[PDB]
Image (cartoon, rainbow, N blue to C red):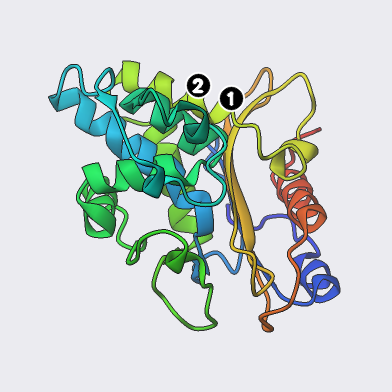
Amino acid sequence: LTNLVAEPFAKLEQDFGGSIGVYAMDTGSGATVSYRAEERFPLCSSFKGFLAAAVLARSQQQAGLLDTPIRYGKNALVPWSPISEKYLTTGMTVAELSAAAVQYSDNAAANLLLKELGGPAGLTAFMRSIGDTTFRLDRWQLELNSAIPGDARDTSSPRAVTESLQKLTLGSALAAPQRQQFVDWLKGNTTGNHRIRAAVPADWAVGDKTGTCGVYGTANDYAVVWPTGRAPIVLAVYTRAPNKDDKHSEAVIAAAARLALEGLGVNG
C-alpha cells in the first residue's frame, strides 16, 4: 500500500536544488506516499506544534495548567514574538502561549513553554511517551534552527512527524478534549497559507504547523486534512539543501503536497 502510484518527487527536488521528504497517510485505507520519508530533516519551528501537544498532555494531569497566568520580562522577547510582545506588560495564560506558539510561531511563547516542560529533553521525553523514537530536540531556540548538514540535533523524519501527528490529532495519545483543542489550534494557524494549505481545496478542513530555519534551504509543514466524505489524511513535507545560502521555497512545499494527495488518489 506504499507508493502504489509513483509521483515525480525527484524532479521536483532537483528543480529546487535540494532534498524533499514526504510522508502522507490515508487514515482510512492505510495507503501511504513516501519519499525520503525516513531521512532526518531539521524541525525548525515545527517543533512548536508538538510542544503545544505536550502542554495539553500535561494539562490532563494538572487541571488549571492551561489557565495559569505567565508573566515574563522584556529579556524573554526574542525576534518573531508577534503575540507575546503585545502582552509583555500583562502576561498571558499557558493556553494563550500555546496558541501563539502554534498559530503565529511565537518564539518567546515557545521558549517559555519549553522551559515549563523541562527543556528539549522534556519535549523529547513526551514524544518517546507516544512511541516516537525518531524525534529529538536538543537545543533551545535560535540555536536549534542551525540546520547543519548531517547534524541530527533538532531533527525528525517526515514519517515520524506524520505518525506522531496522527496519534495526537486522530488517535488516542491525547484525551478527547485535549485532542480537539490541539486540532483547533492547528486549524487556526496563520503562517501556512502558501504551503500544504495551498494544495487543499477551500471546502476541506485543515490544520498545520510550519517551520523555516532561514539557512540551507530548510523549511517544512505538517498537516491534518479532512477531505469531505472520506477519512482524514495526515502528511508532512520537509526540505533542505546543501548550501547555507540556498533559499527555501513555499511553492515546492505546496507542490510536494499536491503530489502526495495525487499519489493517494485523493481528488482535489
Residue 88 seen by the camera? yes
Q: Mark 1 points at which residue?
A: 188
Q: What residue type is labelled 2?
A: Asp
Q: Indicate left or right for 32 with 179 as reference.
A: right
Q: What element carries label 1?
A: loop
Q: Indicate left or right for 157 with 172 as reference.
A: right
In the image, residue 54 lies at what x, y percent?
29, 39
Q: Mark 2 points at which residue?
A: 184
The quadrant in which the C terminus is found is top right
Is the residue marked by circle 1 packed among few (<14), some (14-19), or many (20+) residues within 10 Å? Answer: some
Q: On screen, 22 above or below 208?
A: below
Residue 95 figure quarter: top left
Q: Which residue shows up at 55% across the image and 37% down it?
A: 29
Taking the view exactly as shown, the residue that stands out farthest to the left is: 61
Q: Which amino acid does label 1 sit on?
A: Gly
In the image, residue 87 lies at what x, y percent?
45, 27
In the image, residue 223 lies at what x, y percent?
58, 39
Q: Which residue shows up at 79% across the image and 77% down it?
A: 17
Residue 173 seen by the camera? no
Q: Which residue shows up at 68% across the image and 40% down it?
A: 192
Q: Which of 244 and 92 is in front in this view?
A: 92
